[PDB]
Image 1 (cartoon, rainbow, N blue to C red):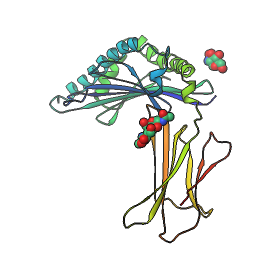
Image 2 (tube, rainbow, N blue to C red):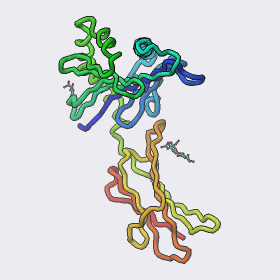
Image 3 (tube, rainbow, N blue to C red):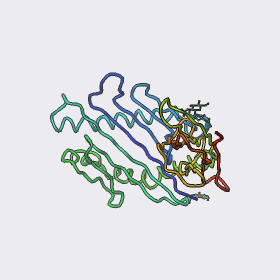
Image 4 (tube, helix red, strand yellow):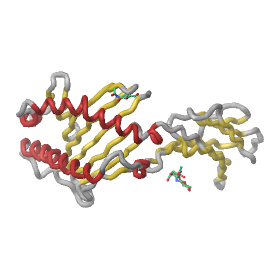
Length: 273
Ligand SMILES: *[C@@H]1O[C@H](CO)[C@@H](O[C@@H]2O[C@H](CO)[C@@H](O)[C@H](O)[C@H]2NC(C)=O)[C@H](O)[C@H]1NC(C)=O
Ligand SMILES: *[C@@H]1O[C@H](CO)[C@@H](O)[C@H](O)[C@H]1NC(C)=O
């Protein structure tokens, strides 16, 4: 088995402006975001390729969970602002947490918060306890550890629940995270009025991201004039391109090369003038 990671990110604004939800939540599986929630629509919604997956998560029930989390998260931010006696300004709280396994073996976990960008507080499941970084975080620590069960719970989530959730998700996400969708390349050229002609090689619909793409002018690996790539989450695919300008008086042969983990041997698409 390989590496897989479940990560959640919560963002709250104490004084949100128009069209910007006061709270937002999102979760990623490796390099793909599989869900999102916000305080406006108030609903846990699957994303990308997970929109078509069934039986992995009762989104209607998670919606309720997210509302719960939201209330706590926002109460947390509220209290910090109360602490610094400054509710006229706008402040943000960001929570990041999750776990990761490698070879069906839990290989890591984390749970930390940031207030106005600086480290606010984090959990050390080895004590187990909360570690404060900001003075206000001391008050939070006190609250979050008022009962002995609390740290036990936080610990249980990081070492049991989260990874359990990750294993489950992996079952329903094989046809997603373990894909080897080979790239469809496409060579094309454009002549800007006044400039040299330029050749653009485009590899698309491939997954994972790691990939090699370069032009060759006479079997010689050229230096790209402009490079670029992207990730389409809804699709769950990657695109990557390279461009080269060709001398107005050049006849040499131009071919595009594309190496990808899903190819038995590299691909070569020559450009026909
Ligand atoms: C995956 O999604 C991407 C983005 O929606 C698709 O890329 C577009 O493909 C159309 C052709 O149908 C092009 O005309 C667009 O220019 C592309 N969007 C851009 C600018 O990236 C891609 O076709 C989809 N492929 C799969 C496997 O469904
Ligand atoms: C780890 O994977 C095995 C199958 O490879 C599965 O039976 C097991 O339940 C998973 N996690 C553990 C150790 O329970």
